[PDB]
Image (cartoon, rainbow, N blue to C red; front, side, top):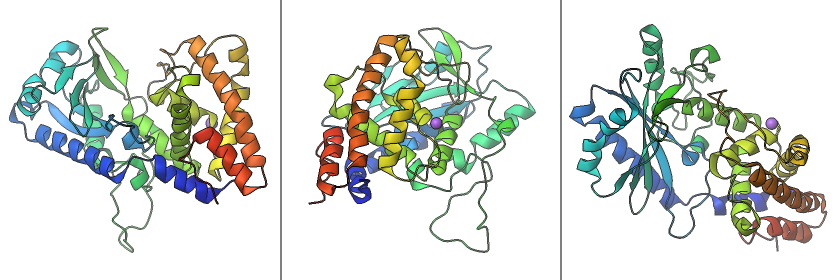
Length: 355
Ligand code: NA
């Protein structure tokens, strides 16, 4: 059976709690506000925005001593062609030393700030364009759709468009018309550049395209996509000893989004469909003992699975193959208790029994 109320309760159980949601909101709010008002950086800092699984509403509740994490991307106007990545990153060391002494560390492509209630990542980026194209891109990056403080789940009406404005419950004759994503010719081939200290160069990154694709795929799947990502992450967590360390995080989310068809009608149907499609689509790659290439949504030349090994991918494929038999039999069951017991064999005790 589909057991839609049971899946709703399960999802409520595996989402980040209200306390954790407020914690990441508070942390990001404070960090961005202190960045905004820091005089030594007001010339280079164009804007800031949120990225990460919590921003995309594809994150599950942290377990035990782990804390929620969000990334604050800092869009600057630095010239990446005339400044080394390390210099651009070190421009932000006085800020961290003033506001987060003893709690920040330098990482490969960002800074990591560790608070007791949240973990923050400060991502310094630059705009490669110049002139009118840079002006239009800055118009986009200063819009309310980019600056938003709400997660994807909290704003169904969100689009990647500089004309989009948030809605607080009610609005009528003013503007009840839904805007759409800006045409791809305005952003798709315009990624930001990001310092890489271990490679010592500026690489391309396009978080806005990733967020936009996530939101559109959730709309095309009637809001089931982010919840399916969460459910699969929870399944992986409950069976971590039987699964390889990777894929996890965004590569796992990307695999899920690739496997899932549009038009999903329920969580159970979506799970079975995405698992069957994953198994048939990558059966040849798996038999080759290889791994698939899957391009990043914003940088087509980047492979999301670049760091995944073929061995880990094939181990994960076998894990999905074992989970898919349980999922198919759970969906096919016509008894509520049997169906819920199979769903619980997949997901654990956070999935409830009807009675
Ligand atoms: Na798909």
